[PDB]
Image (tube, grey):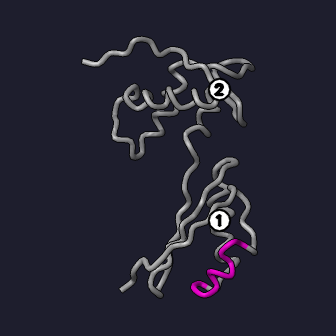
């Protein structure tokens, strides 16, 4: 049958896989493999860049289970433009804070995996009002054009 009778919900920081996870004693009754369940996290979550990535190990009826790591927020990429978080290889010399409409697009592009948008400007329209919540000044977005 294999049915999603239930699923585990937990949250942990990237790169913190330990032998004593929050589901350790709650997974031994399924896989019975701790190390084999941790090594799959230290190389999954850690592979991001300082951020929380909660996993949802789906527990089927009594056959097998699933697992997936949720990627970080778009903000993690916004810091690239200005230069707040760890970053390198920039167009400027050595300054951080405030960017242009070119930077926002530099990220929106790769951020078009599921986004139902083809135009970079059509997918950045939302990215321009995102970082604004953190504390950045959007510039380079004049009176757009729509038909």
Q: Is residue 55 left or right of residue 35?
A: left
Q: Which residues are magenta?
A: 21-31
Please state the horizontal and vertical placement of residue 127, each as a whole percent of the image. Answer: 49, 31
Q: Which residue is mark 2?
A: 135
**Secondary structure under badge 2?**
loop
Q: Are marks 1 and 2 in contact (CB under 8 Å)?
A: no
Query: Residue at coordinates 48% horizontally, 38% vertically from top-left?
Result: 110
Q: Quadrant of the C terminus?
A: top left
Please state the horizontal and vertical placement of residue 24, each as a whole percent of the image. Answer: 68, 78
In space, the residues marked 1 and 2 are separated at their CA atoms by 32 Å
Rendered image: mark on residue 94: none
How dense is the environment of label 2, judged by Cα within 10 Å: few (below 14), some, or many (20 and up)?
Answer: few
Q: Which residue is mark 1?
A: 41
Q: Residue furthest left?
A: 147
> Which is more toward the observer, 81 or 22?
22
Q: Is residue 21 above or below residue 133?
A: below
Quarter of the image for residue 57 reads: bottom right
């Amino acid at each position: 049958m294999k049915k999603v009778v239930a699923v585990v919900k937990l949250q942990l920081p990237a790169g913190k896989a330990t032998p004593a996870p929050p589901v350790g004693p709650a997974l031994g009754q399924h896989g019975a493999n701790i190390m084999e369940f941790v090594k799959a996290f230290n190389a999954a979550t850690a592979n991001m860049g300082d951020a929380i990535v909660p996993v949802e190990i789906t527990i089927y009826a009594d056959r097998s289970f699933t697992f997936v790591t949720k990627t970080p927020p778009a903000s993690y990429l916004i810091r690239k433009a200005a230069g707040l978080e760890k970053g390198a290889h920039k167009p400027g010399r050595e300054k951080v804070g405030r960017i242009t409409w070119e930077q926002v697009l530099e990220i929106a592009k790769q951020k078009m995996p599921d986004l139902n948008t083809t135009d970079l400007e059509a997918a950045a329209r939302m990215i321009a009002g995102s970082a604004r919540s953190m504390g950045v000044e959007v510039v380079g977005a004049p009176e757009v054009k729509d038909a």
